[PDB]
Image (cartoon, coloured by chain):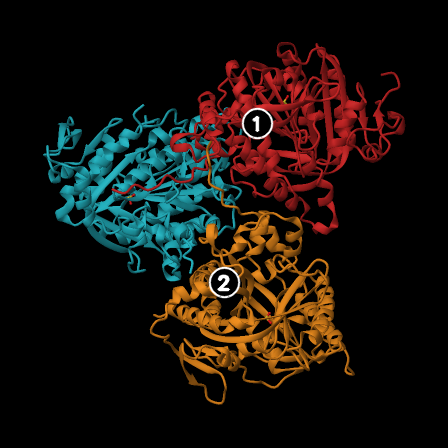
Chain colours: A cyan, B orange, C red
Amino acid sequence: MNTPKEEFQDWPIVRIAAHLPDLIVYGHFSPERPFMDYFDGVLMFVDISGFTAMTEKFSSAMYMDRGAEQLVEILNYHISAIVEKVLIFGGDILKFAGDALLALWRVERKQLKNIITVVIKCSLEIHGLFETIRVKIGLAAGHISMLVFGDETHSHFLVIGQAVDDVRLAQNMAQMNDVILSPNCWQLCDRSMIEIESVPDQRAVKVNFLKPPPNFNFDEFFTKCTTFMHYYPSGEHKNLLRLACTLKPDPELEMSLQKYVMESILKQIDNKQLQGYLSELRPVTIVFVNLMFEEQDKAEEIGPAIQDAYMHITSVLKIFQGQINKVFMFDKGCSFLCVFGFPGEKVPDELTHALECAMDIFDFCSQVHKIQTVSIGVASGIVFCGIVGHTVRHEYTVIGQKVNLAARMMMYYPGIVTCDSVTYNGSNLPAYFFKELPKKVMKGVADSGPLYQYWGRTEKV
Amino acid sequence: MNTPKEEFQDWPIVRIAAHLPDLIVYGHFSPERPFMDYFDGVLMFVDISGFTAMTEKFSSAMYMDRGAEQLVEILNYHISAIVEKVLIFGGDILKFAGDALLALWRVERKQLKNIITVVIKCSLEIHGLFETIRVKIGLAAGHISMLVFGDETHSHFLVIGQAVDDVRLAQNMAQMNDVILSPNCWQLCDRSMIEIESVPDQRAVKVNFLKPPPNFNFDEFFTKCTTFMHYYPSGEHKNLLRLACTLKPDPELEMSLQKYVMESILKQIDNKQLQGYLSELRPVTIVFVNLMFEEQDKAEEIGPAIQDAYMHITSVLKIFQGQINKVFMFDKGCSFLCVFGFPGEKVPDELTHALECAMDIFDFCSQVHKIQTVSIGVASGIVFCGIVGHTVRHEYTVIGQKVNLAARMMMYYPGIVTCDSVTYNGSNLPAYFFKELPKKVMKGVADSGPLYQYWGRTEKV
Amino acid sequence: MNTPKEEFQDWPIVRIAAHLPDLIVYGHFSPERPFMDYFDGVLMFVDISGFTAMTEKFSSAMYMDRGAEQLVEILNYHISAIVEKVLIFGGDILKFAGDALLALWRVERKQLKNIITVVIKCSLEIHGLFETIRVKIGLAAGHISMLVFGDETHSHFLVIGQAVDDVRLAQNMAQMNDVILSPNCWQLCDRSMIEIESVPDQRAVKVNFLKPPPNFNFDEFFTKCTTFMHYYPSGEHKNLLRLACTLKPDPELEMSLQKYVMESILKQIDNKQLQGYLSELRPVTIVFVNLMFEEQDKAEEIGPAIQDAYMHITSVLKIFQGQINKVFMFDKGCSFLCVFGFPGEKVPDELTHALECAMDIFDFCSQVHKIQTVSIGVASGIVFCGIVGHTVRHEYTVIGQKVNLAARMMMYYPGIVTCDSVTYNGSNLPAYFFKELPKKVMKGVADSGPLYQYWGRTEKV
Ligand SMILES: O=S([O-])[O-]
Ligand SMILES: O=S([O-])[O-]
Ligand SMILES: O=S([O-])[O-]
């Protein structure tokens, strides 16, 4: 009796799970919104802005109308390598976003110390890929909250808390090729493994060297650390980068997981759209919404507020097929990256509509309990869209100078709706609906062009 | 000198052969129609109505517009496992159809006894997959006729005879998890292998246990039985589930095999249509044609009649791009499952046309020599369409309550053209073209709604 | 720590490299045009006209509208096998074209003798595939020039010189199953390896037998010959048919290589078009341009002329989306195979436009320095288009009686623009714009139909 080999199982549920972390795939939590949960872990934030800064290079005429295709190929080639390192070291890639990848090693409290060693080694081996288009790494550790929000058809998640705030602060201190540890990470780590130095005006530290004790053996140590890693591929599945590659059809699980993935990605997954259709340089309008809270580390306070904001945003976006591309925590606040124009969702008057939707969002969110400040940046132009990452772990992402610009406008012009010159000029709304703003030098931004506040239709706000 | 490994050979002829049994793939018979041939074998009929009854579940709004995709994924996951068992035990899957899969082990007469043992073991291991959405299994053995019918562009086949009648009768007696043997199967089997019980008012038996003799070794026995299995993958190809996976380009063979496969499937096979385009919940009209004969086990009588009917049906269907999805033998008669509306073949007025085509078919077939009764059921609504089965052995199939309803209408209202309320109401043909029928309780049917006879345009028929 | 296996790397750059020889893939030469380089090597020309003559068979109604699909499947099945032999013997397939495949083993001068032995063995093993739709093989050796020409967006290459002239002359002497050596090949070869015979009225020879010395071991000999083969897959990559399968993303390399590949192929490569869309029987107009030179073995003379001609041709073709499918050296001259109508590039009035473009090309090229004669053949009808060859090495190709006819018209009616009857009749240009020509018997052509000169719009040329 023959024994044929199992076939490569490429079911829709597997393909959906490539777009999600294990935190969600194996999360099994209530469908109630908001949902909050609490754990401990180590975070790694890998600043890949040096790669995504290539969007400019690839809009050159030199690329003969295949800039987007070339961009996605070269980005994925480098980002894949980072993803593989994270996964082989036992990490969960949470999100690709804010010109960064964020990864998590969730463990019980007692194991944070040893897991920090693992993550430092991983970090150093990531830097190792690119010796000779480099990255900066921040590490944090400690208490982490998770929030899941959404409605009956769509779900989003966020991780929150001081360790999350810390990991971005750490990464912002890093220079290229650095690994920076948060103060708490440094307090919790195995100091015998590493040589550090002080970072001026900061309690964060820089790892100069991982130099373990004489009798240390990393592979044996790692094996010990895998006892605490629930989903590390093992046994018959030790050849797989993710256990999620083994997922079998389960309609109730797939119904829950598809809520995290945009409809046009699901169309591709279902082989009802060409696999290359979403890689494009396309004109869009970015509406970047920032919500600041009194206290942004307290999920129990900020979770209902985000949920209420989300319900309104989604209703407003529905009317114009705008989409939410990403939600993430910034140093200050919860940010929604909304896009008007992307998977063939491109209505005419996208600009006047974008500004009107921004104002609606601004007015509603400003009256939500516990939301202290709302800030919205609106920028329009060519952006790269595509599925970025590894075959086994990837996400649809939008990258470009106008993305960056809308993000910086919402941070440098807080409490108002701002727009760029493309949007202002294109809108053909009357000019007294705007205010011309002072020029600010914004980290990452070369020549803003004139920026404007969208004051709105009436003098008396 | 290097020796690179043969590549995965995924030629069009291989892809076409996935849709056909070995009976046809390796049949090499004349292109003359009808064609009849005669052999012996063991049949297994696996009632998968418990899986296909899930079409209802998947039309819920809960499935957010991906019901068809979810349905095909979960069906294929379970049906694949059944198919693999059949193939590894040396069976030929003949058809997926009538909420069942039918499989054949063709052998010389002297080996029927030992092959029945093989098939009983297979049957028990199929039940084993689903312990903890179960199936019922009928087995028959004996003389089997095959009929191939069609024209210059299209071919269809049927297996016929008492063993075929028996295998459906056996399966209809089974409860869930049962294996029922036909009277002849029980007469021909190795009684020392099994413990049976009587089935009330029947000469069929139920297998309680396969309990072989003390010195029996199934793997050694199976190896002996493979001497008689012409196409069992072996040697260099012992890792393949089907020898047909090894087929090489051969234009004369491909011309013959493509005649069995619908044009829209061939479009997919030729990579000229997306691989997911045929998985859909779509509105159609089912026209289910049953032809009863004096004697339905005699291919030499019924073969010309079916051929003549087929020639007329196809001409009538051509005019409205209706398609024949399946042809199969029922307890009573040869049934044609015709569909109006499926691979983007959807003409307007599908309902008046469907009724007019049914009447045409009814009038012509009623005058065909040896056709004793014609019965036609017409039902319209949402049905699941898709390629169902294993990668290596699968078929386009239509599944749904309206399929079931049209099938039961043709059996419970013999000798007439009947239609459901959707069809009657939608047609906007005058009401005196119909007769409102008595309500019958039909096994498998919950609330028919009012049913109608299509009497036709004139009072005097 | 797990070690997952590298995935099958199917990047766009790899897929582009399948369409090109190693000569270009690893060429790294200046982007300046024309570019010329000089080397030595052995050439093999494999006449596959016996396969491509099947286009006629596959336009039969017997193939039910899948002639093109069946043709490409059967062609690729046989041509793949030839390609694998060439590659495993260390050859570089340069082009698929002129009903032939051309391959090159580039080596330093001192190794030509031993490499000829390798190529003769390869040739004999190619014939071996088809014992029991056969091929003819010519071999040449010696000095070879390469020319690369084009503009900022498109590139083409040619190999030139007496060895190239020789390899076609050798192949034209061959009968089926023959291997014919050019005079220089025979002068340079290891005469102890082979038994030859004279070819009447020729200094070329026919290989009767490869009968090496008593102590000869081909595998050991081949291993020695691989020292001189720069890109022979080896070591960790000894399982690959081409090193080019290992190419990694590199935007500057991909920008250079995509210039050799038509835009519609790049669309497929980018998964923005179905993989089967370019296999078709379609009506087109072939415009076959031949340019003859005083001295066609001297790249330094003919290279600027070809470049100047190319610049004009491309400008003329642009206006009507005509494409250049192939450029190659014929016994006499440089030929451009231009096509009007192929990857959905089909403008109305294709015929009057084709004739007007031919005349433009004829008038311009006739005034180019060093171009001695221009001849253009114009023929219109159904042709097979598709990607032909092996997965790892293949090219878009057009095949058909009208291709053949336009090629023979340009050779048998030199110095003029000629067209077939389909073109003349269809154009609805006045009849005095043409001259009806004497009938010539053209090798390969059965019934021309009447042929015409396109004299043009005025009496006085
Ligand atoms: O989920 S992280 O963007 O706050
Ligand atoms: O071929 S079986 O449906 O009678
Ligand atoms: O490149 S060969 O056609 O002269």
Residue sitting nearer the eye, B348 or C449: C449
The amino acid sitting under disc 2 is: Thr
The chain carrying label 1 is: C
Residue sitting nearer the eye, A21 or B238: B238
Tell me the CA gap for discs 1 and 2.
Answer: 44 Å
Q: Residue furthest bottom?
A: B201
Picture quarter with the C terminus of chain C: top right
Instruction: Write down the residue under mark 1.
Output: C211
Classify mark 2: helix, strand or loop. Answer: helix
The amino acid sitting under disc 1 is: Lys
Vertical comparison of C424 with C62: above or below: above
Q: Position of residue A238 (x, y in %)?
A: 29, 47
Classify mark 1: helix, strand or loop. Answer: loop
Vertical comparison of B342 with A270: above or below: below
Residue at image position (63%, 62%) is B341
Question: Mark 1 touching mark 2, by CB under 8 A?
Answer: no
Instruction: Write down the residue under mark 2.
Output: B227
The chain carrying label 2 is: B
Residue at image position (62%, 24%) is C195
Q: Position of residue B342 (x, y in %)?
A: 61, 61
C107 relative to B221 in the view: left or right: right
